[PDB]
Each structure stands twice: as C-alpha cells, then as structure tokens.
Amino acid sequence: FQSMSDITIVVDCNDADFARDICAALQQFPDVTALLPHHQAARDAQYASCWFPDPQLLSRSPGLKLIQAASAGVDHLPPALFASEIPLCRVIDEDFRHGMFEYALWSVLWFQRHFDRALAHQRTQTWKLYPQRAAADFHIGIMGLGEIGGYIADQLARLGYRVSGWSRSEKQLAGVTCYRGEEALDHFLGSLDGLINLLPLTAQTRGILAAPLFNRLPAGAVLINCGRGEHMVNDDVLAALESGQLAGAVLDVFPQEPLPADDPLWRHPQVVITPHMASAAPAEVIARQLLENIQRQRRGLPLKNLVNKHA
Amino acid sequence: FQSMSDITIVVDCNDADFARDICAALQQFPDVTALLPHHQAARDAQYASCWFPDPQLLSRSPGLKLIQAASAGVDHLPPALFASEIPLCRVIDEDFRHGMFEYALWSVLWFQRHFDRALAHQRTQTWKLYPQRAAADFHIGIMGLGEIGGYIADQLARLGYRVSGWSRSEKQLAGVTCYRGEEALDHFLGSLDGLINLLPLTAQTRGILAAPLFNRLPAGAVLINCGRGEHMVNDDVLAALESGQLAGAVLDVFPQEPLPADDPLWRHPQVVITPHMASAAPAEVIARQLLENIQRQRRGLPLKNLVNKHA
Image 1 (cartoon, one colour):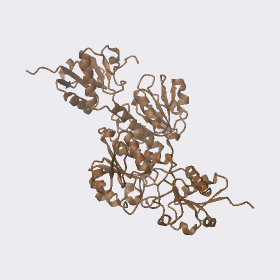
Image 2 (image 1 turned 30 degrees about the vertical axis):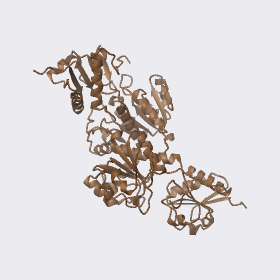
Image 3 (image 1 turned 120 degrees about the vertical axis):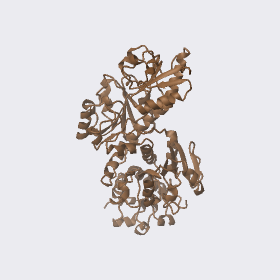
Image 4 (image 1 turned 90 degrees about the vertical axis):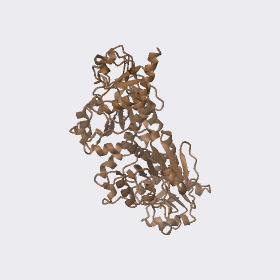
C-alpha cells in the first residue's frame, strides 16, 4: 500500500473556487494531502487553512494542531478558534497588500478625477468637463491603520494626497495626520473628501458606517468600503446618497455574498459594486506559508505570523 | 485719464471657460490687461497665451513679442507660429504632469483589476469575480517618452508594473524597457497588456492608432489615448474592439470636441469616453509663468521654457 502523506490538511473556505485553488497549490508539494471538509478523512486532519470556515471546524476535525487564516485578516474566523488553545497563524504577503492599495487608489481616483461623472454622462452622451482637483486638495481618511491600512495611507501620502488616518491605538505615520480613539472621530471625519474603511469587524465596529458617522463628514463626501459588509447599515448609506451627504460609494463587501440581485445597492446611480475583489492572497503563497509553518512546528520552532487571539 | 497697462495680453483659447479663467488669473496682477481676440485692442497686444488659437493670430495681432502655449504640449499651435521669428514658450508644471499620471493610472487600474467588468456586470446585477492580476503581470507600454510620457513610465514602474516605453529618439529610463524608432515597434507592441498614447501630433503620428498597430498587439490588449484625436482611426478602433484584438479603450481626445452625441464611440460597451479632462495646467500657473517670462523678456533676460520650433 501507499503510506499516507506525512502532512494532511483540511481546506475549509466558503468560496469553493478558492478552496479548490488552495488544495491544488498544497498538492503541488509532494507528501501533502489536502482534503475538503466533506471527505471523512478531514476528521483526521492535523492542519487547516480557513476562510469563513465552518463554526464547527474543531468538532469535525478535533485533532488540529495548527490553523491558518487564508488571509491577513482574521475577523472571518469563528469565535471558537479564538477560545481554543490551537495555534493560529495568518498569511502576510506583499502582493496582497499591494492589491488592497490598488483598489483603494482606483476608487480614490474615480471620485477625485470625476471618472464617476464621466461614466454616468456617457450613458446619455453628455460631454461635461469639471474642475480638476489636485491630489493635495483631496483629503482622504483611512479608518484602520494596521498592516493594510497603514500601508495604503503611506502610499497615498507618497502620491501627494492629503491623508488622515484613524485607529483605536496610537499610530505615527509620516505624512499622515493620525487620530486615535472614538473621541477623535469628529475631528478625523470633519475635513474628509473621501473615507476608506479598512477596520476589522468587531462588536464595536459593527454598523460604524451609518448615519452618525456619515453626518460628521462634510456634505458630498465619498465612501469606500474595503472591510466587511456588517460594517455598513445599508439604509443609512442610501439615505446619505439621497440627501447628498454622500456623493458616492464604492462597495466591495456585503453581509451576504453574492450580493442578492434584488438588493437596491446594485441599482443606485452613485454606487459602484465590486464582487469582493479588492484583494486575495494567491493560492501558492498561502500554500507555501502554511507548509513552512507546519514544518517549523514539526521541528519544534516558533511559528511565523502567529495570531494574537486577545487583540 | 488712466494710463494703459504696461502689459497687454491676448488670450486665444478654443475653450471659452479656459480663456476666461486665464484672463481672470492674469488680471489678478495689477498693471496687466488681458483681452479676448474679438476686442479691437487685441490687435495691439504685445503678448499672447494660446490653446488651439486662431491660425490667423499673427495677422490679427501683428505686434506680438512673445507667445505662450497654455500647456506643456505645442501640437495645437498652428503652423504659422512655428515658421515665424516670434519667441514661443510653454507651461511646465508639476501639478499638470501629476494629473496626466493620475488619469493613466485610473485607466491602467480599470483594466488590470477589472473594474471595467464589474461596472458592466453591475448593469445586470451580475456578481462575477475574476482572477487577480499583479502589477508585475500587467505589461504597460507608453508611447512617447518626453516630459509627460517619461514621468508616467517611471511612476508606473515605481508601483511595480512591467513597463515598456517607445520613443522616436534615444531614451534611457530606469526600470523601463525602452525601444526606439519605427523598426522597434513590433517588439515594443508584441508583449503589451495595455498601450498608452502620449505622442505629440505630427504628420508621421497621425493615424498611428490604427489596424497595423493594433494587429501587432497581443489579442485582448487595452488602449488608452491621451494624445490627440487625430492619432486615431475610429473605424479601426471599433473593428479591433469587435474582433477582440482590443478588449477595451479609454479615450480622452477626439478630432472634434465636444465629441458629437451621434459618434458610435459613445455607445460601445468597451469604451470609456472622458471629456478631454486628463489634465490641464491651472489658470494661475499659466498666468504666473507667462508674466515671469514677459518680465524676463522686458529686462533683456533669457526666457524660460522656450519651444524649439525645429524639433
């Protein structure tokens, strides 16, 4: 008989294509078996790669020794992973962060340079030039200044934008006006032409993109949501767009995905819907970092990119 | 009586709003009079600011001592200005070049990250994720590597794009694969995911964006035209879009502007039309550089940003 692979991994991802891609990238390494959760051998896996995994993972696969979030963020992992003693790591990848920046830059430009108006006017064959707005005269606020948010803020500042940043904790970023804590929200919001959400989803940030926040922005601000769908209160977005409190939104993430065909966001002239595309670590990067960490673990070494479960 | 201003300027621009803006910025300086060509006193102006001026300017205003192109480019000036002995200068401005880059970056992103597909699918409420394409795996070609083109090429390379550049003359740009001359066109074109036109309009570049050029690109390339409308042969663009030789275009400039409501470009699903907005020097920058050069001239000094009429 064939001996079983030394490494067995369950790949528990909500997007089937993503899970399949990660399984294939892991199976490019000899002596590795990658299984989906429906396979009964999944119950025996010693390692897991996860993106919105089953909240019951630890029941279905009770022998797990290392769990990896298939992304830089961890707010898609269920509460049980945080409460267990299984080591939890994440994917930290230059190409992913660069992608999140690309998306934010497209979206900033769309509004600053009025591509939004151009595309709308194109539908009616209307030719209308608007004033040109220099990057120093477009004030962008980034909420959330961790690995991703801080990177984006710094890169925007490097292109010449006026950039403000907001975090729960102290941050110092060169070229960026940094604000800390809820009390500082009015001052962070009150000068912005554009707001970009990169917060993780927690009990405190749920619903933060709502009327109380939008009413502290200057009229005609734009919103860009790259966090989670639960950050948003949808009725409040649509209400802001209708009064002109918001002039537009670019939205990548929704409570349910695919976004249902009937959701009214799809149809608002001032909304751009993108299909949770802002950025994703590639399968091969995920595979390699997971395997490197498995190997470290098997050799008794300290793991890289360990998740602090109490942060 | 009031003595006439020491400085009298005619502002001959094809866009009335632009001419008006330049007149107002010049009139912010005391002892300056700025006139439109219809004013009979225009015939006496000693200085001119021009953007697609009357081909008869030198007849209507025969005492002109210094003529300024209200832009970095000069291909909108009529042949007579090049054949006369009147000094000719241009506007060189960091904010303008940065704007041309912004436009090119929006357009590169639009295609690389499939915002084009997202916006199209949004019209039908279709949710469709596509593969994510890293900047090093998006090969952008910039044709024209002068002040503007070279800047854009360098800035794109700095963001991590694979960047090629093409010029009539020798150029060396760090991080950019530089090609020279017509003979090198097949090699410059044959690897590109995206092509950006920044050429000036001359007898040799007229009609360069046509079938012979598009057929040397790899199928599914994208086009971005920031040069002049005459660079394009429209039928050939539409034909390329229809076979899939081109996957899309972003077009800022047209033989006639406003682009007529009936032009079929307005209606192609894979075309973006923008209203000659890519970038413009601001009125106050124009005004100040013109006045600085007038003052230099009146003091017998060498002028700045002099146009080489034989280049």
